[PDB]
Image (cartoon, rainbow, N blue to C red; front, side):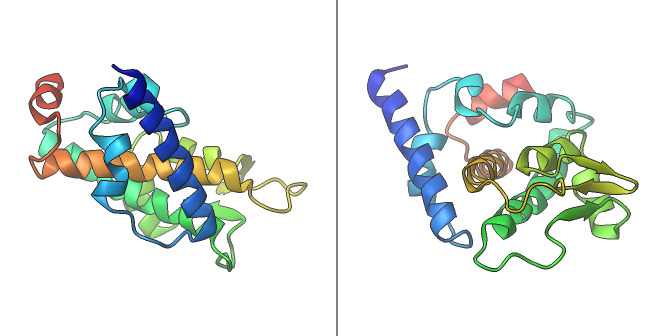
Length: 177
């Protein structure tokens, strides 16, 4: 894995995290994602906040066409939590997540590790039925939220590519499953 690929990787990570801070609702192209998506960098080197290998491995129950979809659905909702925390107007209720919610039950809690991703955003205080930002913390940490959101987006993107039979490393990745 070369010097140029490693440098491109980090430049992309910083550029896209900055873009998410600047305008958290914008869509990103595959071209923008390329330096993070078609690189020869190992998994442990590409995901620095999420343990992406564990998120997949722990949920690798039954048929990949199904569990990759289940993970994608959870990641979509987790990516909206991060984009909303970065938005010039955060939704009301942004400070807390309630587990007793029908969408939450069928999405984020349909995968092992879903709640821990919310913790990485800053929802670190345990509550009777959910998680919240601690009272002493006034605002989200934009750098932390943006890097987590980008990794959630990237992993959703890779899983979507595998489901579309179009991942740059589709064959090697399918053998692993």
